[PDB]
Length: 215
Length: 7
Length: 224
Image (cartoon, rainbow over all chains, first blue to last red; front, side, top):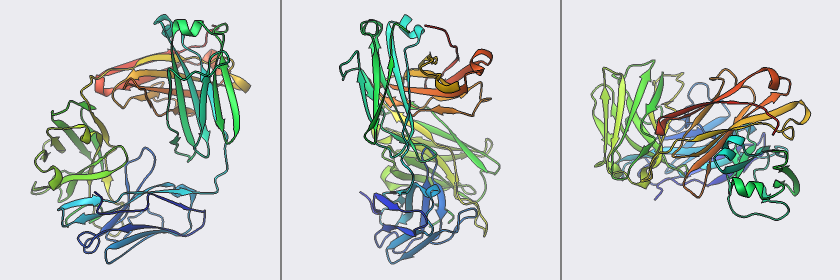
């Protein structure tokens, strides 16, 4: 139950003027102040606007805030890729006697070039072999856009067991990371000649391999 | 309030 | 004016979550609203309540008023939060915030970094750290990757350091994966000039507060 709703996603080009809207009821925005918070991947929310339009020191002047009736708006004039973050309006709800936050809008800035991922496939450490297990670690970093397809193979066939794969994660530089682990027993590992991590991004694919004969 | 404060 | 949170990374259902916030660079008695804010997975933000520094009068979000209590320890310069009868609905990241000075050139709010509290019946477990030693298939065109596998731990978070924080350039520690076991696995790698591989030493400091375990492993290249 959201008494403050915002579009889930919003997109805008660099230099453009974009606005994030916040729709509330008479009991919060209609009569109370609204604050605007900005939050980057892995970061605490950063206060951007208070008392509907006031900027704290240090906040770029490209951000402006308005409010009328029971609606509020955040405006970025001159969109920068630096601005890619999540945005929340925040107000006080009289009906519910509590401070509330909006649904949040994820703002992405287009025009960033496509970047192909760097892929690193580590074999199992000999210690972990000593523990009768074998984990193959496939790290996929610094790609854009954030969709990537990962497939594992033992000697030639696909394997759909023991495979665990993260969702891609917005890194601090607005490109994405991800990682996939293949969990085997030491015997399974020594029962195939090669295991391979095949990561496909933007219709182009690269495949790294590890082989017990090398260790 | 700068942020969440007195109503 | 900074803030930081301490508390158990895991709490069992129906038990009581307890958190502490330590304040440095400003007094806790000051006439300010000190709020506890939680952010669930799914990035939903909820205001739990605040306490006013001078009187200590508190106001709670009515949806949680029974289970919550917020208080102040003037001698420690401390803020405290207790939430009873917790369920999986309280697994979230928790922050302490001070409104911040009301002046023409304020920096704004003040937020702690946030402590993730996971509510689950399953027991805490520390990670086993095995080294990710570079192949030459990893030493392609002078620079090799070498890392630490922080495997099979619960619950979040773990934090990794390289040479006790003395080496920062070229470290990417990846977000952890939630294995279908219910356990997390994570990796941290550092990219290095191949020349260093014979001379320098790379030790990763894996740290896991919820299970009180800390592991210090060194990574070494060895053929096979």
